[PDB]
Image (spheres, coloured by chain):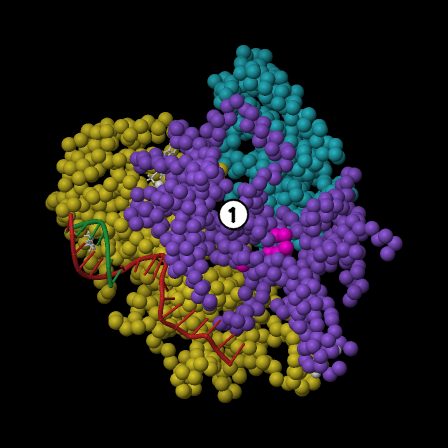
Chain colours: A cyan, B yellow, C purple, D red, E green
Amino acid sequence: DYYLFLLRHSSLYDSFYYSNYVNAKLSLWNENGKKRLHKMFARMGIPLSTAQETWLYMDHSIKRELGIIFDKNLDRYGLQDIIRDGFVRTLGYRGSISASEFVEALTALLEVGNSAQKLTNLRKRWVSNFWLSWDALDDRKVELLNRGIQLAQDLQRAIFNTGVAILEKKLIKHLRIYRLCVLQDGPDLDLYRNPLTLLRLGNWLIECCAESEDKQLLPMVLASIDENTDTYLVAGLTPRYPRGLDTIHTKKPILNNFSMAFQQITAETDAKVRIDNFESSIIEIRREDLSPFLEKLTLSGL
Amino acid sequence: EELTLESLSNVKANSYSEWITQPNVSRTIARELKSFLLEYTDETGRSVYGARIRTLGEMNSESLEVNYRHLAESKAILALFLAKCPEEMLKIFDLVAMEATELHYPDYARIHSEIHVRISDFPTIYSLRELRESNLSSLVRVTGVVTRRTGVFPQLKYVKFNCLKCGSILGPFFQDSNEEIRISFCTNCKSKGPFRVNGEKTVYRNYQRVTLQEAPGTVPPGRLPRHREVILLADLVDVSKPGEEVEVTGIYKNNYDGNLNAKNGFPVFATIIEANSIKRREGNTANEGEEGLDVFSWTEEEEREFRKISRDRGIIDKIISSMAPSIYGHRDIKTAVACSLFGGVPKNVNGKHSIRGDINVLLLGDPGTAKSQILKYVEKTAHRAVFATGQGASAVGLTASVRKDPITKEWTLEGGALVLADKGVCLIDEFDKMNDQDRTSIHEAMEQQSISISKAGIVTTLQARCSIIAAANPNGGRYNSTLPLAQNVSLTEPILSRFDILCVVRDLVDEEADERLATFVVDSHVRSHPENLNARQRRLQRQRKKEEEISPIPQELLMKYIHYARTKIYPKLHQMDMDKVSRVYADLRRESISTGSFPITVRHLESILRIAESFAKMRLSEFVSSYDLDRAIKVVVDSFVDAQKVSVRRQLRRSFAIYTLG
Amino acid sequence: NDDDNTEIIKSFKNFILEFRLDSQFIYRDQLRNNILVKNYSLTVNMEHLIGYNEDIYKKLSDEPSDIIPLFETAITQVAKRISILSRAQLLNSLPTFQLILNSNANQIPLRDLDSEHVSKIVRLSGIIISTSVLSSRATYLSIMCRNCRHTTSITINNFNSITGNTVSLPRSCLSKNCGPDPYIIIHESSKFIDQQFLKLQEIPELVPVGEMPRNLTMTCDRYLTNKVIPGTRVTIVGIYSIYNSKNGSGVAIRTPYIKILGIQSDVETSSISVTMFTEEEEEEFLQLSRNPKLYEILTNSIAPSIFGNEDIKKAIVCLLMGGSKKILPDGMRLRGDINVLLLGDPGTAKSQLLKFVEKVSPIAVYTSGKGSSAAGLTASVQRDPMTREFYLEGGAMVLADGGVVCIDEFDKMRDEDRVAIHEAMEQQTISIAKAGITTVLNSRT
DNA sequence: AAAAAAAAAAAAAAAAAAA
DNA sequence: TTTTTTT
Ligand SMILES: Nc1ncnc2c1ncn2[C@@H]1O[C@H](COP(=O)(O)OP(=O)(O)OP(=O)(O)O)[C@@H](O)[C@H]1O
Ligand SMILES: Nc1ncnc2c1ncn2[C@@H]1O[C@H](COP(=O)(O)OP(=O)(O)OP(=O)(O)O)[C@@H](O)[C@H]1O
Ligand SMILES: [Mg+2]
Ligand SMILES: [Zn+2]
Ligand SMILES: [Zn+2]
């Protein structure tokens, strides 16, 4: 199996286009990325009309030969780290599924489904979505998995659409210690009220930042806005090494000090924050209180 | 085997055709052609054909284009061979093209097995009248107008037969697209009998034949045109459209006919043209800027230079100053025209709301203001240009019309003028004198972008994306400043409101302005005087020196820039001032008809948005910035201000100074 | 040669009789219910076919016309097996069962069809413009000779691989010294099926730049006939094949056409005069109708992007619902529709409502008052190219009978064209007296 | 081997006419 | 001068 977004349920072209690893490796958010992708497809020899068909109806001979095609072509672009070994579950004549696809469907179903009062309503719809995902586990239901798969497609599309805008506008400010970016205004901001969706976006962003010529591993701070509450949701993200790296430089995983920094600043100053997430690296802050708080975080020992 | 190029100079057989097919000759020709297209260095020191192959691989199309003069400058004997014997040359050249292409893309054969090489521009040009006996079985270059297009049908490429009287399977056979394969002795048995086609193992092509007349601007006056038939093989299908002027490079061939010999009493033969390359020549008659099948297409380095020069400061200033470098003044028009020919982004909300994304422009003023020259330059500039004038266009002419087919004997639709303008511009001269029945028919074309016909039992709806640029003259031949716009023209609100940018140009008496204009005009006349390495490149550099003194950038680069900007870049609009634009629109709703005469509606707000999007397009940016919004609002407010009476012009000008503060 | 056919038929029968989800054999139950209500047809979903086995799908993909008849006779074999008792050894009025497919492959537009799709299964969508009348086709022919005078039966399958595909008449007689083909067709004691022809036009918003829409021809037969009406968006699944043109220009031409295998429609032929909705959908409609304020829900839902106008939206909803048709003992009719005219200033978005209203109503046509004529709306009299006989072809207002018509720029139309609609909207019946053709044709809109 | 065409209906452009 | 109607 390969690091591909819903390979067995979307066309191979869209799979390569939305796969985060290929995105990071070849910069598909501008034109040269698409040109290199088309060159790769041509050198493989799959037609652009063929590669844009569903995996079921796509040609059987090249379905069989896909492994050899990848082995012989991917070396030039250096994407050979996309091939791995995984698990596949088959139930009679129903079809085939894989662990990565199933967990992505579950994650998307958790994300999307169906002042204090609004916060309580959000926290209760989160539990409702959790129970819906739980019920989706059993093998007697598949209409709660097809919906999850299509919603995963939609969510990944929206995340890509927002990330291309971020990297185009160059909102990533490089401070002395830690990078910072704030989504002041844009599209589809209402989706990012979910911490897991925000983490997915941040994971893609940190992958993109890592897959560059920069040799600095800096923590990242990301913020959002919901005009209904007039609050900023802030999450701290750790740097990540390139996936294709040896294990010798893996003595200790990169730690996360953001929870300690947040608790120390909240203890020493009377900010209007609300630290109640089980993930201690995610806090809520006020719009007027954000900027001085950030200053403090800059001036504090990390 | 002496595989030397010089040995091809002297022929050993009686004719060229029987000498080319010689086994010794063919392989030498193939290897020389290979060494040509693998190594031909352009002026930049890089093989242009390498870039051509890369682009073809990216686009996985079915046509590789070879410049003729490139082949002429090096290995000219092969150019002569191709000019005299096309059939025996093109096959070998296709084979070497496949070899070269799979040198870059191995296993590309799964995409396509063969290629159809096209020649760019032959040196000699013939018209339909100057066709003789000698120019047969050789390349010709014919200009014409398409009249009747047949359609798309499949063909047989590799024909095989099964002879059942002996059970003999015949080998694959070709076809020449105007004959029938006739087999006499039926393979080794040497016996005549029945056989079947058994086309379960066969491969298909598709062709399309069309009627080619003479260009009405080329025929001698008061004479009649000469028709010919053109057959279009695979990959050239539907490239040509009815009603357009085209130029075709092809092969002239002859064939026998029965009824032709019947009606004349003499052994006369029919002739058809097998198309080999097609180049559109509608509107854009300036055919000296560059060569090639398509002048609006770009190479990769041209895209790189587009990106490089799209980022410098004040690029909009250079672009606006680089349009019509032979007309003095009229900065506002020089800006409105650019904003009109870039256009906006069409908007589709949920598939149930449609917002037009193109800008109309109207000009108005006294005679002698060079409006027609601007219109001519616009026609020369855009990718799709349609020119009309005054009484010379009827309402049913601009729009599609219902016609009865004189052969198939029923009704059918005929493409109107606006249909050719789809994805392009339609230019109207003398807008005011056109009869109102000929004027009211384009409301949907301006606004809804749709054409609907319910005539003679046919109920269909077409599609038209056209930007209308019009010019006219006010009542009495001169614009009276002390009257509102309602008493200066005969148009009404419904037609006026559809126009986004409306410019009024006045003729006024001045001293130093007249002196400067006269100096510029005289220097322009003395500049364009016909009497002031390879000769052609020295001519080209002289032309470049002549052009660089008034235009900041060369025009062919500008045309390719226009095409690139219209094709790829799509701006997006996020960070715009809600209250600023809302207050501006409220202010324009105030005053206006409530104090004056000019009508203002919600469509002008969409016009402001579209102008801002166009300004964003000018810089090859995906996101609108605030400066572009400022420029758009400045243009709109200025256009509204300078269309009022002189009694209130200064007062309104000082009133509106806060939104365009800058 | 026969062994391959037997193996293929056996494999298809095994698939039919062995496929099951959870605790249900879906296709066997489908066959039983179909036979009970005299709908001799079966529907195969391609995903199930692929999942059960891939080699059978490969064989169906390679040669459709050669393979389909084997499946459509295996179906009738299974039906005879599971519907009729052998009674240790009758009517047997079971013809060959019709096979209908459904799939979810990538759509291919009309203009992208080329020589590489010959004899392949493709999926496409368009708009229906013209429908031919029904016609008969023979499937079982009784053949009698003249000299030897013996009887024979010929079985005809309706699938064509080559252009001919037809054994006209056997050469010589069956065994003295007869002629070449001394056979005649016994019209009595034969079996006939029904066939219809349709025309497809390209979808408006996929037309390439500066082009005119292209037409294509389709053939449907048996139950697929009389399912669509002109002017309804459809999705077709079938085979793209060719037929020779001897009666026709060019060399080796072969006009292409489409053989319909499956049709999906947006209206599901529901209005084409009884109700056939399932209980779930009817219950849902009743539940929505039970809402105490659904009037405001519908009023808001009319053109959500248009702001401010309220009475016009209420009037549009009232028009969409329509009145109540009436009749009387003495024959007097009473109109059952309402006609709304918008007469307003520019810039108020009048037509933006017209195209949305065209989108909502199940039967709607949009046309401009400038590009219209009296003869081009009510009824047009043509004459055939070949037989010259005059016939009546309807225009626009009759094409949208039983729905609503969207006219914009009502003033720009000529005075002569604005008088023909008087009776057409006051009495809903248009009368034509041209070339000896007298006809009272109805139009309710 | 050949029925093939006079009679209608509908769609324009030009010119002249009336207001 | 303009729009209408007829050829
Ligand atoms: N700066 C200029 N401003 C105006 N005219 C200029 C200028 N420079 C040159 N000209 C000349 O003035 C003439 C104006 O064009 P032309 O006489 O064809 O009519 P127009 O002004 O376009 O419009 P109209 O036909 O309505 O009178 C052209 O011959 C053009 O070459
Ligand atoms: N109330 C409104 N809300 C939103 N948009 C509006 C409204 N009124 C007009 N518009 C805008 O007007 C624009 C053009 O409208 P449109 O041309 O359809 O108007 P109309 O009244 O039908 O005009 P016409 O009488 O000239 O045919 C649209 O882009 C639409 O967004
Ligand atoms: Mg309108
Ligand atoms: Zn033989
Ligand atoms: Zn007999």
Image height check: is B545 above or below C328?
Answer: below
Q: Quadrant of ligand 3?
A: top left
**Which residue is painted at 53% across and 71% down in the image?**
C247
Q: Nearer the viewer, residue A57 or C264?
A: C264
**Which residue is painted at 49% across and 72% down in the image?**
C249
Instruction: State whether the magenta stretch is mostly helix, strand or loop.
Output: strand
Left or right: C120 in relation to C214: right
Q: Nearer the viewer, residue C5 or B325?
A: C5
Image height check: is E4 above or below A97?
Answer: below
Residue type for callout 1: Thr
Left or right: E1 in relation to A260: left
Q: In the rendered image, is residue A193 in sight?
A: yes
**Which residue is painted at 71% across and 59% down in the image?**
C69
Q: In the rendered image, is residue A290 in sight?
A: no
**Which residue is painted at 29% across and 28% down in the image?**
B587
Residue linked to disc 1: C232
Q: Residues within 10 Å of mark 1 (few under 14, many from 20)?
A: some
- The quadrant of the picture occupied by the C terminus of chain B is top left
User: Given the image, what chain letter belongs to the residue carrying mark 1?
Assistant: C
Q: In the rendering, at what x and y percent does residue B168 appear? A: 70, 79
Left or right: B144 in relation to A63: left
Q: Looking at the image, which residue sits at the far front?
A: C330
- The quadrant of the picture occupied by the N terminus of chain B is bottom right
In this picture, which residue range is highlighted in magenta? C217-224
Q: In the rendering, at what x and y percent does residue C147 appear? A: 71, 79
Q: In the rendering, at what x and y percent does residue B546 appear? A: 28, 58
Q: Nearer the viewer, residue E5 or B58?
A: E5
